[PDB]
Amino acid sequence: AFVGTWKLVSSENFDDYMKEVGVGFATRKVAGMAKPNMIISVNGDVITIKSESTFKNTEISFILGQEFDEVTADDRKVKSTITLDGGVLVHVQKWDGKSTTIKRKREDDKLVVECVMKGVTSTRVYERA
Image (cartoon, rainbow, N blue to C red; front, side, top):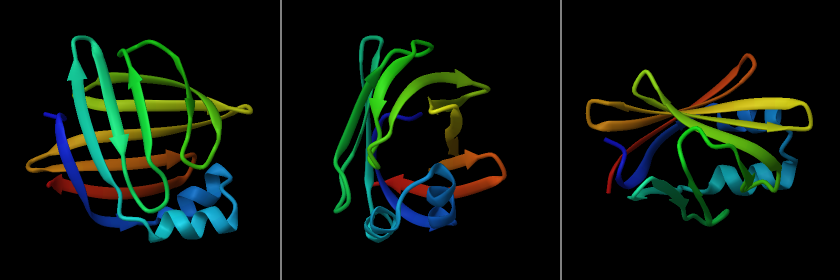
């Protein structure tokens, strides 16, 4: 369902999501300009998600249900836990008393990414490269 190389097709409300997370102006602008890909692979029980763009190249590798340390593209040091829950890949990040959730869902031929922090949602839609 999730494995593949995915290209961004649309993005909505991303700047306001970033402001909620606490991202600063200069970083918001560079992140907003980018058109990342998302490359999802598996090796045994270890899942890797990579993203390449003009803003940041990032990579995380993790086991479902196992908390891990992540350094986000905007340089937050977070505690992350990623699970499958109702068929959705659910990524919770916790840092400095705050939490945000990134939901990666498969909907027909798309990978829909909903980034939620409290009342603020950004939706990014990807399709296979």
